[PDB]
Amino acid sequence: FLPILASLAAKFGPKLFSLVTKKS
Image (cartoon, one colour):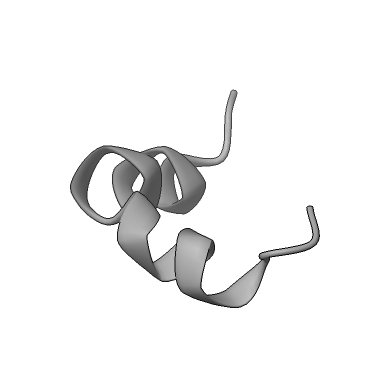
């Protein structure tokens, strides 16, 4: 399989990742 929560977060809200993981 693949990590569903990460895919859902990437489709809906890559805004949250952009706020936290600014280095990477």
